[PDB]
Length: 126
Length: 123
Length: 123
Length: 126
Image (cartoon, helix red, strand yellow):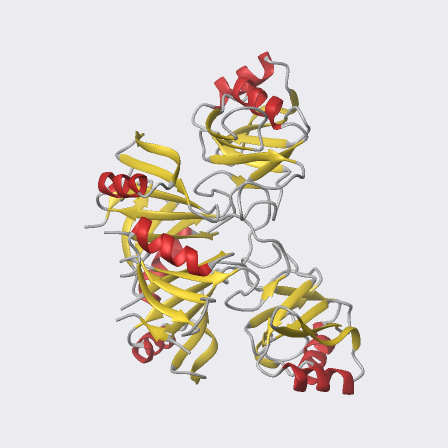
């Protein structure tokens, strides 16, 4: 396979900071290294997303082909995640709930209104 | 030492693994969890891995959207013997084995979920 | 006898083939056309085929839409030696080689077009 | 990798017949075998498409997840293709033209308004 998820923000500078603080993401790579952000790769703890500016020339050759509005992230500890987001006063759309199909999850909007869903042996044959 | 992994979503991974092993002759490498219904399985094709996942439970971060039919492309050495096994197993043949411009010998089969598999004699 | 084929679109297939052979150690199996710039190339990974295509020229019938970045998943036997070659070639490392829950050793690299490649020590 | 292209029609019966006659497609598989069409696979001469009803229960488990409105088909003989479509009086959106990037193509709408685009050595190393 599938697409890399890419997110477009009016200003990625504040978005990167907001996502790291509220959602506990970590910055892996940023471009340019110094100054205003044109591109950044963030570890969500359930995979990486690309964040970019709405418009401009793109730094990545295959970028700008799609833009995601609703992201699904699988997280190890969803309660602690839920606790950090609400303590920061994020726009919770749906409070943390057990779903009678073996999942617990919540919905939340980020600082620019994009919807995020956060949700929670081996036998090798030979 | 390298293996390309192709991720495919199935409604019933238990039945999909069984089907894929029986019909295509893939080999189960790994299943998760150990007990009960499979949520995730890795299958060796002999040249690449098929990662079977339950619908709605992708391998990594994803954008929200529907379960769609995938086209899978496979090169095989003996496409005639391959077609004969697929047919004997009762698979749904979409395009029967035929010659195509150049040296191509290929056929097309739909799996139990509806994914399309194209098997070609090394193109 | 089987080989899974993974199709990937590149703006400059000539440079992509060169890059992929040099950086990842893939092997050129086939190029089309014979003379001039490559429009299509097949690359052997040792366990699966990468089909390089020019952007806007897909392998088969398609729905209209943009050129997007793909995530490619690869299992490797010696991920340490693999990471050392990628780095020496100057590839853009997104996630440096690290241990992850279970027995996982993986890293992530972006290719010249921007596709993401995840290399893991047999998961 | 990519999706199979699936097309939804108000009545697939007429659509299948129309596509075979005007666009020169060939029916590979139909469901059910007898009676009204719920599902059909058509060879376009540049790959296969799935055609189905708008709604209903689906016969294919992975179907109904997407629906394509604009299809791109690569054809060996685009002039003959163009000639057959116009002789049948299909809604040509864009007449057959050489494009200064090495391609010749035309745009055309089908009987239910979906947009179709029709467009036109080996060295093994080892």
